[PDB]
Image (tube, rainbow, N blue to C red):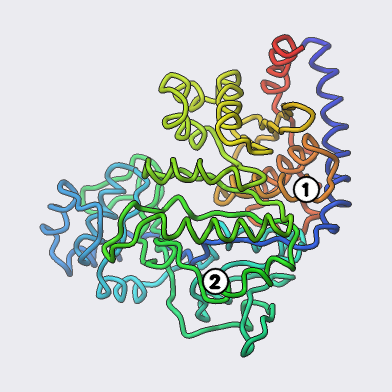
Amino acid sequence: MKESLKDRIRLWKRLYVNAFENALNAIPNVKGVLLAYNTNIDAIKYLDADDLEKRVTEKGKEKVFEIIENPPEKISSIEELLGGILRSIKLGKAMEWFVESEEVRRYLREWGWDELRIGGQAGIMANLLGGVYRIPTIVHVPQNPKLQAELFVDGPIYVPVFEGNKLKLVHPKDAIAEEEELIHYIYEFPRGFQVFDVQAPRENRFIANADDYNARVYMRREFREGFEEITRNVELAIISGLQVLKEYYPDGTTYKDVLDRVESHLNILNRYNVKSHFEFAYTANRRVREALVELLPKFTSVGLNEVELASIMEIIGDEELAKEVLEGHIFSVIDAMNVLMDETGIERIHFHTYGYYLALTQGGGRQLAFVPTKIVASPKSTVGIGDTISSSAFVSEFGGGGGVRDALLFASLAAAAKAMKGNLERIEQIRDALSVPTNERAIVLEEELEKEFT
């Protein structure tokens, strides 16, 4: 190893330790955070071969196998549910099909699950920001039956309820309503899982989505009528869930009907000087994707990864730039971030990928912050990591936590800790991530930025 790398390694150890201290001191000063819009139930089943074979045989094995070769890419029957699962196994391929049949939803609920956890970006960040970081959190829960409300951990997590004409903030378990279970059924299998003659070449999962409400970004009454009072209780907002929007729905409504309501919410946030952060998850519909870019001027900040930034370059950049961004080639990523800032005038863009983060901020002219991250070799869990990174940097920076780079370092530690441990319970546990080595390939990469950027 070059001695200059030994020196940089020692400098990054001290920056990481100080950034963790700064985050612990600044996070308690965050008055509150608003999380919207997507919360659901994730039901995990670890597939059993004998069970799955019996269920295929009950319904007609030949009908099921016809579906494997001729997939409907939607679920209207139990045979289509079973055929989709077996196709996911055969291809070792992540798949999600929507369940458009109430009879199949009854079959899914009866079949059950091994593990239940909160789903949706708003919901999982409620458990992290409120449960682990102890930031007072108000979360949008489109449908809050008992099965949904029990999945929130203990802590300062609140939902709004109307007491006649007055808005109260209560724990979700104290606001159970006569509402739909919004369940995403997740069928997991390992490499080598075999039913009949079908064998998985890698681990993967098939998702049966039984959730009509987050599919169209349903907003409950308390958020449509109490939004201004809710806004008075927070300092920050993180907005997610709009990636699902379609241009047209069968009832004749459009994506713009939803985005008009989001824009009204952003106008209220900005009137109260709430700092807002948009999670620009992959939006398959190109027209909605363009509309979301046109909405970014009303946000303080946006977060995205290499897939998400490449996707946006397909509509405001060029195909060659998207291809380079997808591989995380840093000088193309930087160009793409400046293209997005030029297009929108947004104050802040947080890019995260394997090995490093960037933050581009508009201040005394544009500043670029870079950190090498901490990679966990074999993570105990991979779910919610991107949202943890984006939300953790945003709340510690705008919470007063040592500046832009320090907030990125804290997000790197939170991501490593969640990966090491599977599930976080207390913010003190993130200290254990300091022992994860800093990515030395990314440490050395910063030398290329310094030569380029005097």
Q: Name the residue under label 2.
A: 224
Residue closest to the far bottom: 164
Mark 1 crowd level (few <14, some 14–19, many ≥20, 10 Å Cα)? many
**As shown in the figure, which amino acid type bears the numbered disc 2?**
Arg
Q: Quadrant of the C terminus?
A: top right
**Front residue of 451 and 31:** 31
**Front residue of 173 and 279:** 279
Q: At which x and y percent is residue 160?
A: 63, 76
Q: At which x and y percent is residue 385?
A: 60, 47
CA separation in Å, label 2 and label 1: 26 Å
**Above or below, 64 relative to 166:** above
Left of 368 or right of it: where is 355? left
Label 2: state its secondary structure: helix
Any part of residue 191 in sight: no
**As shown in the figure, which amino acid type bears the numbered disc 1?**
Phe
Left of 4 or right of it: where is 369? left
Label 1: state its secondary structure: loop
Q: How many labels, in total?
A: 2
Rendered residue at 65%/57% (across/down): 423
Rendered residue at 43%/77% (across/down): 180
Mark 2 crowd level (few <14, some 14–19, many ≥20, 10 Å Cα)? few
Any part of residue 434 in sight: yes
Q: At which x and y percent is residue 418?
A: 66, 50
Q: Name the residue under label 1.
A: 398
